[PDB]
Image 1 (tube, rainbow, N blue to C red):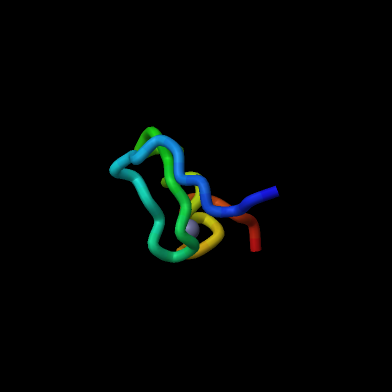
Image 2: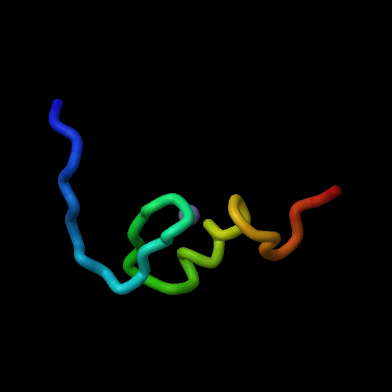
Amino acid sequence: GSSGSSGGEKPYRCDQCGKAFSQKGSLIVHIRVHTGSGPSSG
Ligand SMILES: [Zn+2]
């Protein structure tokens, strides 16, 4: 019951939403929500 608890301190951190990832690819699958990434139907 207490927000604000960063854990990992990874280099991969999206500035669009403010998230963190351990790998690069993992982040690539997230960009789909921000910028047109890979296929996503019409
Ligand atoms: Zn993001």
